[PDB]
Amino acid sequence: KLQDSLDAGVGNLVDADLAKESAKLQSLQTKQQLGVQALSIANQSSSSILSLF
Amino acid sequence: KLQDSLDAGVGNLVDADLAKESAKLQSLQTKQQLGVQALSIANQSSSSILSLF
Image 1 (cartoon, each protein chain N blue to C red):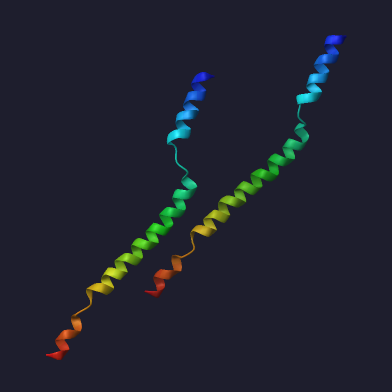
Image 2 (spheres, chains in turn green, brown; image 1 turned 180 degrees about the horizontal axis):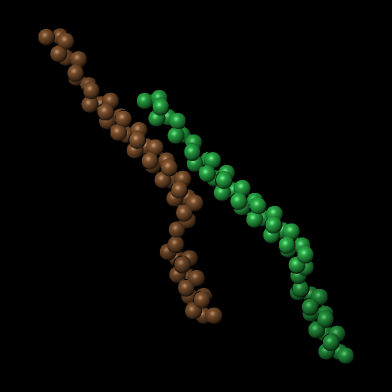
């Protein structure tokens, strides 16, 4: 009985909640996809200078 | 496990960041296109002398 209590205590200390990690993973994947597109938008600046010359 | 650690370490040593290389490539391509036009502008100097004679 004591060993079961100690195992449960350590698990309570260091375990995670995967239900929350799923939501965080979804939001972060969407944000990374948006960040790549934002970098692509930022790269195409200064390309309009060539028309002046 | 140790072999995985060593491979990751070497990769950390010698790998590049392609997100930055994309931006640098765009800027350098634009600058080269502008440089060719600038050289073309510089060539056409001294062509106006012939009108004096």
